[PDB]
Structures are given as structure tokens and as C-alpha cells.
Image 1: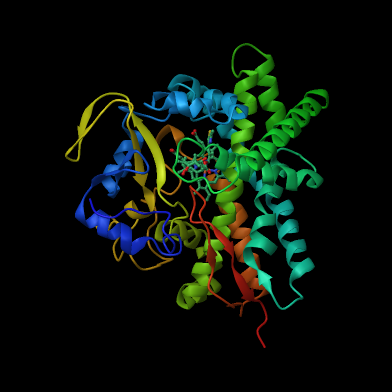
Image 2: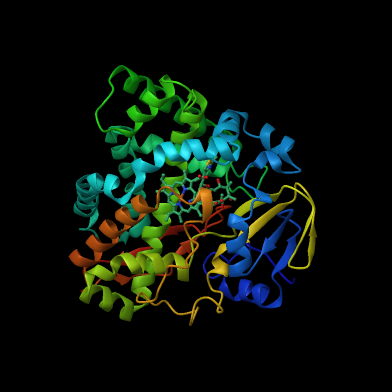
Length: 403
Ligand code: HEM
Ligand SMILES: C/C1=C/C[C@@H](/C(C)=C/c2csc(C)n2)OC(=O)C[C@H](O)C(C)(C)C(=O)[C@H](C)[C@@H](O)[C@@H](C)CCC1
């Protein structure tokens, strides 16, 4: 049950020695600063995802009151968003939007994503320094979500800001060390919600064929299928959930291929392996700092612990995914392995709706960059930060065509 310090300097860069220590010594421990139990092993993590004794709604938490008062601008999003809705409401909302996120539906986005990837590399690949985060990955995910929502590129920076702020603001009162000023967070959240109201009112005015937002609006207008608050919360969550995560995937992919020349040469030789490799990036080195949370609906015993009702539980994803009893050679980056058991996109009713979008964006972004600059080399050690949810890479400086 030893030493868990996920905000220590060095942890985001390389958390694996620390959490192997934890995982090898115990399946469960109490994280005093996080005020919650932490589960360290694959099977325990996997099960809790599907186990209905554990809720997602933060309203089940013993500290619900404190959490709901924090960032009142986000109260609606917390009550009516995908995490807060009761299971039958959650199923309903998911049944509605899931069709818009399949591989086939998101395939339409392919040309716009490639165009964005093309102009980012055109506009900045000429200087000495190329920052894979600042100059590349950062400009991609919002373009994608905005194409899916049919929002003009001029609004991209406002929504990205909103997405990233919202993801952090939702941590305030929930997770220990949100690394930003409230007033700044709150302003980006406010402005973003305003922008969103305008996007939605325009779409109701000018509804479109084969369009996610119009479909959601048309469901809201007809007999009870989606409330206005559910709808707004849903679009807001999609923007916030899909912004930073994908930035980190793309960056961690490039990093991990630069670090493993063998893996890269394999993906060069069989471009069809790119999809598996991107899944193995998340498996071998998951972008999450700690993981995700659940809340005990009732007192119960679990892996030798007496968990009380309302107590929070963290699933230590990056640990579970190095669990040697499920993955062979868990500590090797192997782009040929079977990655089916990866929990990186969740399991159960709350399984990530954006998985096909994240994979498409990253295949295009990571594929393109290595095809057009095959001899790319890391110019320096990646700089990591203190995002409360993510092992966030702030910069990843490389040399595209090295002398
Ligand atoms: C590689 C990037 C991504 C990762 C690793 C990821 C991971 C996850 C995970 C693990 C969950 C479940 C969390 C839990 O059960 O507590 C989830 C839920 C979610 N993800 Fe993703 N996601 C990613 C990208 C995206 C994108 C691009 C979108 C765009 C819409 C998205 C939208 C969502 C939403 C809305 C939920 C809530 C689902 C629900 O509660 O029903 N994600 N994601
Ligand atoms: C990868 C990941 C992204 C989901 C995204 C988010 C805010 C989703 C969502 C749906 S409805 C709603 C209000 N939000 O959530 C995030 O990007 C970060 C979370 O907002 C905060 C609350 C900061 C966290 O640390 C949590 C515990 C985070 O690590 C878990 C939830 C991450 C796995 C899911």
C-alpha cells in the first residue's frame, strides 16, 4: 500500500516504476490526498467498469454537495451530462448519439482532417524547431470535432480553450490539484458555453441534412427523447472530452515511435499496422495520470477492503495496462501484439463514444508526419506538466529533415 504521489515531478514522464511497486504490493490502497480507494490490477479494474454496485454519477459521492457547488457555471453539465445522468437516462442519450460516432459515420471527416494536417505541416515545417504538440497535435482535434459539428475554423481556438478549460474545471473539488487559476478557467468555460448556445441556435434556424447537431435538435423537439439541458451538456462534453485526450494520443504516438526505431520501421513496412500501434501506444503508455473514478453505491468488501457507500474509487489505468498476468512482456512497446484487452477507451455503458474519431485523427496525423518526414528525430527530452487527469506533454521538439 506504499507511496502514491502522482503529482511528484518525474511521475508524468515515467510513472511505471512507482505504480508497479504499488501494483505488485497490493490490489487496493487508500490515497489520502485523493480521498479515495485506488485499484491497481487489470481484473479488478475491468470488473468495476461493469459492476453496477459502483456508480459514475458524482451525485453518489459522499462529497457531492461540495462538488456541485464548485464551478456553478458547470452545474448543468454535471447534472445532465453523461457522467451525472441516471443509468436509464444515460442509455437513452447514448442510444441517440452513438450512431453518429461509428467508424463509417466519422469516415466523412477524413478529407478535412488531412487538409488540417497538411496546412499545419506546410505552415511550420520550414524552420529549425518543430514542436509536435504546439505546432501540430494542438491544432488537430478541435478542427475534427468542429467539422463533425459543422462549425467554422474561425471558432476553433475558442472551442479548444473551452474544451481544455472545461476538462480541468470539472476536476475542481473532485481531484486534488487542478493546475490553473479559477478565474481564467471560469472565463473560458463561460465564453465557450456562450459560443455553444449561438452554434446551436444557428443550427435550429438553419438545420442541415445528415448532421449530428440537427439530429440531436430534432430529437429534443419531438416527444421526450433528449432535453435541452441533456443536449447542451452532451455537446459540451464531447468538446471537452475530445480535445486534450487526442492531443496527447497523437503526441505520445510520435514520441513512442521515435523511441522505438524497430516499431517505426515495422509501421513503415506495413502501414496497415498503424492502427494497432496507436492502440498499443495507449496500452503501453497510457495518457492518464491516475485513471477514472467510480463511487460505491453501498458498503461492501473488495480486494480486502471495507469500502463505504459514497466512497470514491480510482481505477489506475496505466497500471492495470502493464499487468503482466494479462499482457505478455507488459513493459515492451510491441505494435504487433493483441491489444484487444486494452481498457484505454473504457468498458461498459460509458465506453468512449469518440474512439473511432480519435483513431482516425491519430492515424492521419501520425501516418502523415512519418510518411512525409521519415527521418524525423527527437531534438530533446519531452517536457511534461501537472494536468490533474493527464500525463500532459507540453512540448515535443523534433527535427523533421536532420542535416
Ligand atoms: C484517445 C483519446 C480518448 C481516450 C483515451 C478516451 C477515453 C475515455 C474513457 C476511458 C472513457 C470512459 C471513462 C469512464 O468510464 O469513467 C471515455 C468516455 C468518454 N469519451 Fe473518450 N476518450 C478519448 C477520446 C475522445 C474523443 C475524441 C471524444 C469525442 C467525443 C470522446 C468523448 C468521450 C465522452 C463524451 C465520454 C463519456 C461517455 C459516457 O460517459 O457515456 N473521447 N473516454
Ligand atoms: C479520457 C477521459 C476523458 C473524458 C473527459 C470528460 C470531462 C468527460 C465527460 C463526460 S460528461 C463530463 C462532465 N465529462 O474528462 C477529463 O478530461 C478530466 C476530468 O474532467 C477530471 C474530472 C479532471 C478527471 O481527473 C477525471 C477523474 C478523468 O481522469 C476521467 C473521468 C478520465 C477518463 C475519461
